[PDB]
Image (cartoon, rainbow over all chains, first blue to last red; front, side):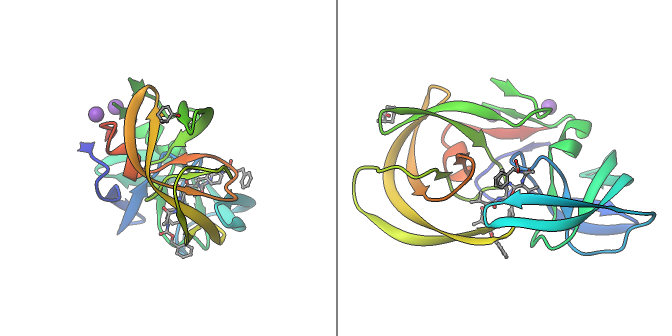
Amino acid sequence: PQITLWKRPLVTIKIGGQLKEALLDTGADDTVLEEMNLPGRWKPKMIGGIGGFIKVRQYDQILIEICGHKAIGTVLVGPTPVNIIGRNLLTQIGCTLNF
Amino acid sequence: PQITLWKRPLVTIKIGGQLKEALLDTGADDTVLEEMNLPGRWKPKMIGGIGGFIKVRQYDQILIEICGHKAIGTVLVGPTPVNIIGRNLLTQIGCTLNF
Ligand SMILES: CC(NC(=O)OCc1ccccc1)C(=O)N[C@H](C(=O)N[C@@H](Cc1ccccc1)[C@@H](O)[C@H](O)[C@H](Cc1ccccc1)NC(=O)[C@@H](NC(=O)C(C)NC(=O)OCc1ccccc1)C(C)C)C(C)C
Ligand SMILES: C[C@H]1CCCC[C@@H]1O
Ligand SMILES: [K+]
Ligand SMILES: [K+]
């Protein structure tokens, strides 16, 4: 797809058979999902944003489909207001910024 | 140009006669720069993100050059750790996500 920026770049993702809406976010190093249940063990991670820092759970090698493209990688889960797809997964799906 | 996402999409901008480095950010509704004085009047605004909300100063009709592409729009000024070029200006330079 080509996504313009007039509105937020929100796309459908699927993870654990569940469809969710998420933000394609070039200003995020990592992908951070709203609270939800994932499999396996997690490890702690702190991420910083505009208002300060939050603690999130890091899951590795997680299956996620983003607008139909499969990616397998790190997903953080925690108190984010919006599902955010970060550069770690945008790279796997071949996403670039162009002007 | 085409900007890959293996690293943060940092570019040179010019604003108020100053060169700065800023992040091309598809997940930002608004453009938010570190503390600076800009021409004209301002009004307070709260913006939210990972970690909560910060108070910023809003300036309107601000000229900016992003990678040598001119744009004009609202620019917010406050305690951000990174200069962020939001969708309000990414639209004007013809910026799109492609995969
Ligand atoms: C690891 C990392 N940053 C990093 O380098 O860490 C080092 C650091 C951190 C803090 C201080 C000093 C140094 C990073 O990738 N951070 C992401 C991030 O917050 N990125 C922000 C930019 C940034 C980059 C580095 C450091 C700090 C900030 C965004 O631009 C990012 O694109 C967010 C994503 C987002 C969208 C929507 C909701 C919440 C988060 N946008 C924003 O925060 C923008 N806010 C918005 O566009 C508005 C208006 N949002 C909004 O709707 O807020 C709703 C809300 C609801 C409830 C609570 C709070 C907010 C902002 C840049 C203007 C994160 C989501 C993984
Ligand atoms: C007018 C202002 C924005 C465009 C480039 C020069 C200057 O800093
Ligand atoms: K384009
Ligand atoms: K691409």
